[PDB]
Image (cartoon, coloured by chain):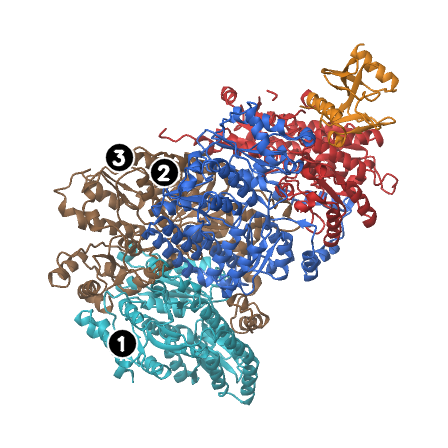
Chain colours: A orange, B blue, C red, D brown, E cyan
């Protein structure tokens, strides 16, 4: 569609930033980013649509400060940040994994930069 | 239970019957502890020679090392310069551990900062971390200089200190003229003394490499003194006192004796004394450079001989009698100043103390450990005292140092039963003192556990510890002692002979059993 | 729980410090390998005063430093073969160890070392519990991440070792002390009061803790958590999985100790409550005498504290019991020279690194991390020592001699 | 039996089975020893309070005194002058004992002569003995001045030193202008400190009494320092160092720190340093005279205030922090020289060491003994450290000194449980430390026999000894320590805190019993 | 050293003395009947830094002090008892303060009042307090100091009265320091006190079971355990050492001494009078034994065994055979490092001539000796046991002895503590021949190993090779 969501979970005590990302590549939910995308609907509507399509029955909140906007051929696509509240990491759904930032080594520069910006927004 | 008139701390509060019964119930009900006979059998096995061969076959396991990492020595070197902040580019836990270590040893505030390198810097490097850390450090603590070292993570990910600092200066985070010397200090190479060497070489490079076209050797008629990794406040002062008595102009580079001995007058001083930047910039103009601890100041020696064009004398550490004499003669030859009568009288008094205490010091067996230069100086002094060093252990020593110490031992009749161990930790020394029992050990506080183990075998097998080295944690104000020069030699001799005398007094304090030898005059 | 500003003299530890030094280190019967270079284990060797009972070097290894001592070749080519050889040598030289825990240092997670596979292989070969902990120092912003990672390792490797075992004789008065690290014997001073109440302390970890006690923890009826910050994860996991209720207890000062004892006894039958009242009556005269002796010389003095995660907010009760004034979930239960001058605090309580700074500034100081080489400070027996140390530090003449008489 | 590889001295050779059997046969066959149960019962009785009441009822018996005779102090005072020979008119055994005592304490050659008065002198006096002794002493050892004291024999028989010396000079045995000061030192009056006072007063009288017409107070702009009976070389050196730091001109009268620390260089020096005769002759020209130990320099104070017209300040011994401060301010006021920043930094460092070790020193209970000024200075320092001097004993103290020490104790919260004993010996102190056990006892080597006694009751009852005082015989080179000034305060503080730490380490070295408190960091 | 050179040295060292001092000292320095060569046991020259002691030192500190079960009172001021407290290493076995009182100082602490009005009432009160506070003492000895004999104090009457009242043996020893010229008169006075008060306490008692192998060790003061090392060898020979005083000695052993069959006298100088008295009265033969060095020990053991039946001689041969390998190994190890070294000694009454045995056993040569308080008989015994063209000094002064050593320049010196530091400064290795330099024992086969080890430790110590600054 037109929106992208980076799904994260930060522990209130230990501040462990885990990222729920697809196992097939990419860093964004629900689908991967267009190949040519470079760094350049309501956000709550995007969050609820992602929750409905991915069968996420958890408490997901919108980090309104983290707004990014990339350009894909013929479209300016905002991407937002969705944080998972609570105290326990939920079991990852099918096709998704709960990676850490140091576990992003070997992934392309674009998604590593996206995760770095998320980490700076939340912990830094 | 507690009595308000005789309140007891953990010892001996936990020796009470109720606490003993509770601990026994805990052990017998849920700890699933091995039987006490089994524990005794295993301990007896660990004190045998078969366990010694099994322990000395170790090649991948290190138990109770006697060394630290390079950035600790780098921080110690950085602390010796005027208004200089040690800045360790890397994780903050390393800096916290360095500060805790130096606080426990010196019992003084220790200044050190980090850029808090985190997973983000693990993926992308610490360039932003370096910029922000340099800016915040300069804006907050107002240092005249920031001396940069590295932790293991920065060296592993490959952070270029030179490029990072240059980029920080170019983008306006710090002024272009602000002195920011740097040194790469990989914690997996060498030990803390190597870190001290790297930091000193980096600072000397930063201050002298690009301004050697107007430097003439002997212009200021002074002698540069590089003390190396030194944790005795008296060692910095004895060198200065002896050089001032000789009338010799000197420049003690990296002198931290002032910031580590700040007076308590209701005011906190982050910076106090230290080597000035002008002394470093004028260092190549000196007559010569004398390295107090040459066996870990190798990169410094190479830089001084190659760039400063100084004929660095081949001097051992000024520890003991002969080596202090050689150091004084070399200083006199370089400076042209005759050795004064005060130093001759001090040497005579030291020899007098040696003659007084030789009857008790002769023939004693010592197992000593520490840094290479300190260990070799202590071995030389023990040989001069008639003592027999039997277990010379140096975890951070090399083969050339071992060969030099073996040559020193072979030159004395008292080094016949001496073995030099390099790359061996304190668990090796435990087996060494269990199988070949010496009279005493000489080392840092980490040996206090070995004395606990030997006493477990029996009082006759106990090997008392003498705390000469780094770090000393279980005693107060021992960092103010001296080990260099005649004064340090007298202090060491007094400590050794008095420790022998306390051991003899304790062994002969049994009434009607061993008190016949409890002599008043000893 | 955010990043620390670069270039500042913060005292925050690493994940390795929070995992090896705090959670795993006090376990006595297990051997903990500081996998990586030599500095981390050496600076953390016997640093924290987590007291224990055992023969060091034979069956207890708390104050010992086991390390891989990484060199350049171990960084270039990895340290997995070295880890396997080290595990073999540990088994050869220390046969009475009941487990091995490999605490990772910074280079381990950066050079791409699979310590989990080595741990699994060597544990299968030696029939020993080897726990790989990825406590690399760069991970996280403080020791809290170390606590979380160590708790995850406990849950995933040690906690479920007796899930299918039902040979343990359980009683309705089974409690487990979690988060008490026995700093100066605090855990013992709490366990004596708990057992005098009729309760059976099946597990007490990590302070004076053993692997058997950790394995037996899921078999208790109540979990008494001292440090919530470091064991909240494990307490919640045990509550969700084994259905064991957990509650927080505070034994600092007589009022807090009495309230916590009554609250704990309220979770059991009337016999435990009667025994708790009897214990309170027994210990009343002792702390009453302590207050009568030390409150007069401590009344009115003002306090500031700044400690890691738990002690900043739970030490107030003992201070008020002595007549002394004190001036995200942790904050829910000044909240960080000129300010110090305006309020003129009589005492500041923080760690060793700030201890000497505040000594130089002239304010009397108390090490709130290691009890200033004293203790215990918790329980009725520890309240006397705490009051004595308060009087010793606050009223020492050394603080009145800072100014030279000629200035 | 002996093994040539490991030769055993008396300990533990006499612990072998054959020697034990031989000694057991000797005891059980011919010694007629009391049964061991009887010995144990009597020893237990001696450690009770009833035995303490019996012991403190003593009126005529002295057991283990803590004092010496006047001529010893007279000899020590005489040794502090330039090329001066101590000459004790009386029996030679007294001189032999003085020389042996000082040789065992200082481990140095001590020069002292006697006229060897015998039974013949018991009926006719020692006039011929004095003449011959003076002539032989001047001809043989060539001293610049002979300082004459007396033994008990010469005082009992009533030998007039003035008349004897006048006749010796008149009859042609020594030159009429040769300096021969004399002092009557009755060994049955006072103690060695009284002898020091008498000898110093005699020397000052001899050199200044008849030449006071041309003396103006404050002409030479210097301050006279009278150290009294001092047996620490560091005490002599610290006063000179502190006065030189302030830039204050001083004259240290009776300075023996040079002849008691002569170097070993293949040459024996009978005389070294000391107060010159010109310094003593120019002493009345000083601004003021400061007595370092005023509580045994009362005769010297009377002479200085009466003859020299010097307003001697009422200063305590410069021991500890407050009294060192008072001494420094008084010296600054007299000389007009402001206290330098180096001394302020030294005071701040002492305060820092006080704050660093206050957690280990506060509340500790000490039983101390020694000379009056030293004891009161130690008590003041202990009160400044938060320690409790429960048992203060001074055999040679008087009622006024006891009142002063009681006034000092009542001014501090830590003197509540403190009692001052004057005229009591070390057996009284043994009873005190058995019935009211302190944590440590501070004193000379003679206390090593009390500690053993306590150890015979049990390890829980043992009172360790800290060797600070005179004489120290069982330790080497402790006479070079310092007890005066800030430096002496730091040395004493370090000794006390480290002794406490060794005791704690020893008490917690039991494996699996008390090693839970065997903390690496203390 | 040529003899003419020794005479020239003596003349040169005496050149600086006054005429009276020179003429007196010329009779006390000789080159190896005593009267023809050396003059001994005479007055010491005033003001010449004498090493001699007093009669109190030779009586209380030497003969009476080592007795453990007795309490010895230093009657007089405090100094004499304070300086002699635990000065001598006369080892003993006992509970100090309960049944043994060797290292403890008992004194009356005389003041001006006691000097003016006497100290007899004070002495009686002191004896009462001693009996009250130390009930397990087996006897009291009152050692007089210098003031006692000058103020007209009658301690004999007090001793007799209090001993009769308390049924205790109180021995008054008038050992005033001014009496005599040295400690030899102290030895004589102490021996007379032993004979007159303690020795005859069991003359009418016949309840001791005696054996034909009864010997008594007299004059061995257990300096570092010498007496024990001699007694072990004596008892391994089959002899029963009934009495061993003063070292580790008891009053019961002193009383039992007249019941022995032989008196082995170690120190002839201090305990020759008592040995002669016992031989004349009780008919007990006495012989001198020397256990210093292996050769002397073997010769003395054979001579002692020759006084008994064949079984004792066979046991002596067995003991010598048993101890042969140990001292042979000691010699083999230490003689190479001690061969050819020259020694000089200045000791008190007995040791200067006794110690020459083990030095030769180790390959050393003695080139000079002397005494503090010896008599003519001691020098008569010494000249036979020393080499030719050597220097003998009687009551040598400080200056004389330093010049002597500066001229001979030996390799080792054995003397007291008062010259130890002087010779340490002059650069000559020194061994305390009085207290064994806080080592020992030195007597017997076990003591020979310690003696050789100490000789090698001191003589070959590196500290003597660092006395010259390398820039001078
Ligand atoms: Fe000396």
Residue named by callout 2: D324
Mark 2: give few (<14), some (14-19) or many (20+) Cα within 10 Å: many
Quadrant (top left/top right/bottom left/bottom right) for the C terminus of chain A: top right
Q: Position of residue C396 (x, y in %)?
A: 49, 33
Residue named by callout 1: E29
Vertical arrangement, residue B371 with respect to residue E305, above or below: above
In the orientation shown, which residue stands out farthest toward the front?
A: B213
Q: Position of residue B75 (x, y in %)?
A: 54, 38
Q: CA distance from mark 2 to mark 1?
A: 56 Å
Residue at coordinates 34% horizontally, 79% vertically from top-left?
Answer: E378
Tag of residue D77: none
Helix, strand or loop under label 3: helix
**Mark 1 falls within which chain?**
E
Mark 3: give few (<14), some (14-19) or many (20+) Cα within 10 Å: some
Residue E422 falls in image quadrant: bottom left
**Mark 2 falls within which chain?**
D
Quadrant (top left/top right/bottom left/bottom right) for the N terminus of chain A: top right
Helix, strand or loop under label 2: helix
**Mark 3 falls within which chain?**
D
Residue named by callout 3: D334
Mark 1: give few (<14), some (14-19) or many (20+) Cα within 10 Å: many
Q: Nearer the viewer, residue C39 or A5?
A: A5
Residue D138 falls in image quadrant: bottom left
Ligand 1 falls in quadrant:
bottom left
Question: Looking at the image, do the residues carrying marks 2 and 1 touch, with CB atoms under 8 Å apart?
Answer: no
Q: Position of residue B295 (x, y in %)?
A: 52, 50
Q: CA distance from mark 1 to mark 3?
A: 59 Å
In the orientation shown, which residue stands out farthest toward the bottom?
A: E310
Q: Position of residue D96 (x, y in %)?
A: 32, 63
């Amino acid at each position: 569609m037109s929106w992208r969501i980076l799904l994260c979970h930060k522990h209130p005590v230990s501040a462990r930033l885990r990222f729920l990302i697809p196992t097939g590549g990419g860093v964004v939910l629900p689908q991967t980013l267009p190949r040519l995308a470079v760094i350049a609907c309501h956000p709550a509507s995007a969050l609820r649509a992602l929750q409905e399509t991915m069968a996420l029955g958890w408490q997901l909140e919108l980090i309104g400060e983290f707004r990014l906007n990339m350009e894909v051929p013929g479209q300016i696509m905002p991407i937002y940040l969705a944080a998972l509240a609570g105290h326990e990491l939920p079991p990852p759904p099918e096709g998704t994994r709960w990676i850490e930032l140091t576990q992003s080594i070997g992934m392309p520069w674009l998604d590593r930069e996206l995760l770095r910006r998320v980490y700076e927004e939340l912990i830094g | 239970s507690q009595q308000v008139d005789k309140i007891k701390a953990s010892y001996p509060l936990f020796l009470d019957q109720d606490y003993k019964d509770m601990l026994a119930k805990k052990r017998d009900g849920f700890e699933e502890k091995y039987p006490q006979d089994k524990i005794d059998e295993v301990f007896q096995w660990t004190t045998t020679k078969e366990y010694q061969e099994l322990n000395f076959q170790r090649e991948a396991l290190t138990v109770n090392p006697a060394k630290a990492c390079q950035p600790l020595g780098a921080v110690l070197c950085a602390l010796g310069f005027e208004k200089t902040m040690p800045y360790v580019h890397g994780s903050q836990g390393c800096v916290a551990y360095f500060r805790s270590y130096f606080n426990r040893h010196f019992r003084e505030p220790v200044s050190c900062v980090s850029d808090s390198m985190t997973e983000d810097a693990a993926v992308f490097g610490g360039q932003q971390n370096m910029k922000d850390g340099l800016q915040n450090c300069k804006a907050t603590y107002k240092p005249d200089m920031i001396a940069v070292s590295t932790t293991c993570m920065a060296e592993v990910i490959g952070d270029d200190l030179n490029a990072f600092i240059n980029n920080s200066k170019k983008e306006g985070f710090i002024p272009d003229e602000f002195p920011v010397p740097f040194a790469h200090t990989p914690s997996f190479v060498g030990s803390h003394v190597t870190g001290w060497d790297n930091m000193f070489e980096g600072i000397a490079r930063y201050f002298t490499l690009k301004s050697m076209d107007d430097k003439v050797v002997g212009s200021n008629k002074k002698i540069n003194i590089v003390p190396g990794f030194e944790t005795y406040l008296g060692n910095f002062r004895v060198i200065k006192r002896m050089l001032s008595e000789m009338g010799v102009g000197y420049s003690l580079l990296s002198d931290p004796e002032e910031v580590l001995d700040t007076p308590a007058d209701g005011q906190f001083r982050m910076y106090a004394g230290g080597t000035t930047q002008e002394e470093m910039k004028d260092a190549p103009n000196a007559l010569n450079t004398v390295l107090l601890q040459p066996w870990h100041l190798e990169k410094t020696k190479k830089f001084v001989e190659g760039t400063w064009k100084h004929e660095v004398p081949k001097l051992n550490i000024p520890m003991g009698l002969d080596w202090t004499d050689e150091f004084l003669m070399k200083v006199s030859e370089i400076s042209g100043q005759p050795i004064p009568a005060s130093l001759t009288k001090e040497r005579g008094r030291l020899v007098d103390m040696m003659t007084d205490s030789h009857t008790w010091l002769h023939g004693k067996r010592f197992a000593l450990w520490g840094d290479p230069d300190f260990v070799m100086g202590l071995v030389k002094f023990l040989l001069e005292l008639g003592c027999e060093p039997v277990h010379i252990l140096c975890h951070n020593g090399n083969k050339r140092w071992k060969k030099a110490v073996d040559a020193i031992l072979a030159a004395s009749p008292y080094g016949k039963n001496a073995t030099v161990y390099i790359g061996k930790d304190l668990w090796h020394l435990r087996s060494l003192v269990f199988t070949d029992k010496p009279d005493f050990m000489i080392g840092n506080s980490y040996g206090k556990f070995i004395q606990r183990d030997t006493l477990h075998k029996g009082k006759e097998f106990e090997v008392p510890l003498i705390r000469i080295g780094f770090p000393i944690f279980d005693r107060h104000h021992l960092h103010r002692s001296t080990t260099l020069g005649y004064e340090g030699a007298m202090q060491i001799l007094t400590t050794l002979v008095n420790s022998i005398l306390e051991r003899l007094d304790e062994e002969t304090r049994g009434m009607q059993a061993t008190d016949y030898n409890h002599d008043l005059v000893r | 729980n955010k990043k620390s500003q670069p270039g500042l003299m913060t005292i925050r530890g690493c994940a390795y410090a929070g995992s090896k030094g705090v959670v795993w280190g006090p376990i006595k019967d297990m051997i903990h390998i500081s996998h990586g270079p030599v500095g981390c284990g050496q600076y953390s060797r016997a640093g924290r005063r987590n007291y224990y009972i055992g023969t060091t070097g034979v069956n207890a290894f708390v104050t010992m430093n086991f390390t891989s001592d990484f060199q350049e070749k171990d960084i270039v080519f990895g340290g997995d073969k070295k880890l396997a050889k080290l595990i073999d040598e540990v088994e050869t030289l220390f046969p009475l160890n009941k487990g091995i825990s490999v605490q990772s240092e910074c280079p381990i997670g950066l050079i791409g070392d699979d310590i989990e596979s080595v741990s699994k292989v060597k544990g299968a070969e030696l029939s020993k519990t080897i726990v790989p902990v990825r406590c690399e120092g760069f991970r996280g912003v403080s020791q809290s991440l170390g606590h979380h990672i160590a708790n995850d390792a406990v849950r995933d490797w040690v906690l479920g070792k007796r899930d299918e075992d039902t040979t343990f004789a359980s009683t309705p008065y089974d409690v487990a002390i979690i988060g008490d690290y026995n700093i100066g014997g605090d855990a013992w001073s709490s366990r004596i009061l708990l057992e005098e109440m009729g309760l059976r302390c099946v597990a007490q970890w990590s302070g004076d803790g053993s692997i058997s006690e950790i394995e037996l923890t899921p078999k208790v009826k109540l979990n008494l958590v001292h440090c919530y910050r470091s064991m909240n994860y494990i307490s919640r996991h045990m509550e969700e999985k084994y259905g064991i209720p957990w509650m927080e207890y505070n034994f600092f000062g007589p009022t807090k100790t009495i309230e916590s004892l009554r609250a704990i006894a309220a979770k059991f039958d009337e016999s435990i409550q009667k025994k708790c009242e009897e214990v309170i009556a027994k210990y009343k005269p002792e702390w009453e005498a302590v207050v009568a002796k030390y409150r007069p010389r401590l009344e009115g003095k003002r306090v500031m504290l700044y400690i890691g995660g738990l002690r900043p907010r739970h030490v107030i009760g003992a201070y008020e019991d002595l007549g002394m004034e004190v001036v995200n979930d942790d904050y829910d239960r000044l909240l960080y020279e000129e300010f110090v001058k305006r309020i003129k605090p009589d005492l500041i309580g923080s760690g060793i690194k700030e201890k000497f700074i505040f000594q130089k500034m002239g304010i009397p100081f108390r090490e709130m991390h290691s009890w200033d080489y004293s203790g215990p400070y918790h329980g009725f027996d520890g309240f006397a020592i705490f009051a004595r140390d308060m009087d010793m530090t606050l009223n020492n003449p050394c603080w009145k001699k800072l100014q030279a008489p000629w200035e």
